[PDB]
Amino acid sequence: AELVASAKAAISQASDVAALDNVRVEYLGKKGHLTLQMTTLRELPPE
Image (cartoon, rainbow, N blue to C red; front, side, top):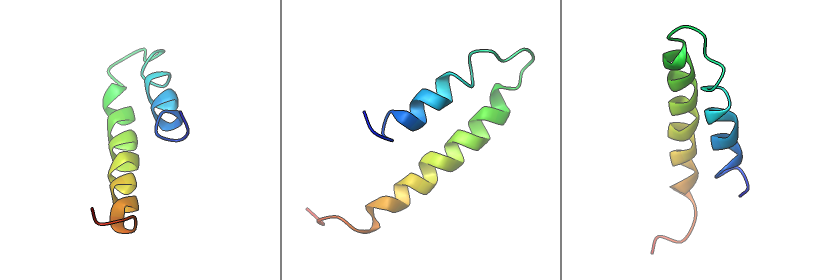
């Protein structure tokens, strides 16, 4: 429930009060966050 869901907590909440079709602006901003979070696995045990 830390960052794994905290970034998803700020993602769905940002996609809640979307007036127009601004959900793509949230997607490009959140997919850029989760893709930069895929670089976190550069460390960690390889198994």
